[PDB]
Amino acid sequence: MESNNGIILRVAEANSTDPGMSRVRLDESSRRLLDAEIGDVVEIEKVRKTVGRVYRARPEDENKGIVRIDSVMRNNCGASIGDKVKVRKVRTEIAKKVTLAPIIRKDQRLKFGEGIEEYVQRALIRRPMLEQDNISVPGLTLAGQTGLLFKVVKTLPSKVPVEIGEETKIEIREEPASEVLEEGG
Image 1: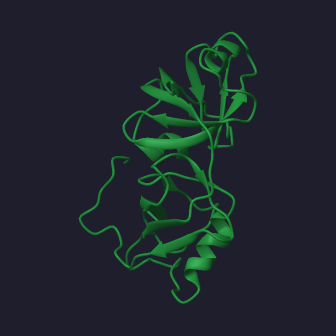
Image 2: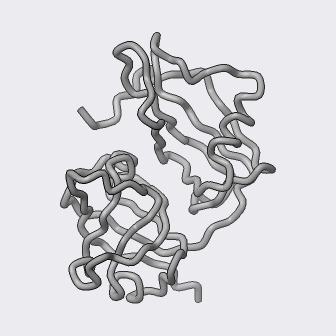
């Protein structure tokens, strides 16, 4: 009935900034082989599950089996360039409750508590969320810190790409990257 599936292709990326980790540029066949329409919701899964949206490849002929994403999107699952990831097309929904875990240590500057759940909702509001996903912060930092990224582990939706809204509920835990070392350096 629903017939919801995706395709396995090769992760793409270039030294250029190529900003936009939530946008997937694909060719007409990669988009139309299933149903993906302009600006539909696409999920990606190479090593782990990730979310994103469909875009048109500049070269509507080379993107017939490669997806160009930003470094963070590639870092979200744990894959390298040219690896093989599976992209499944889906739609978005309003997540009602999502929990995440900022990874830092003695260099943790992005923690406040009290209203932090709103601070996360405000920053991540109206955004696609997928448990076990990962996020990053603009070019900001302090001493020699490491990690300093958000690690989502629990969402209310069916583990499908959902969009956060001002009404969505959030949870921030106080457990940093203890016993946690995701591949990447």
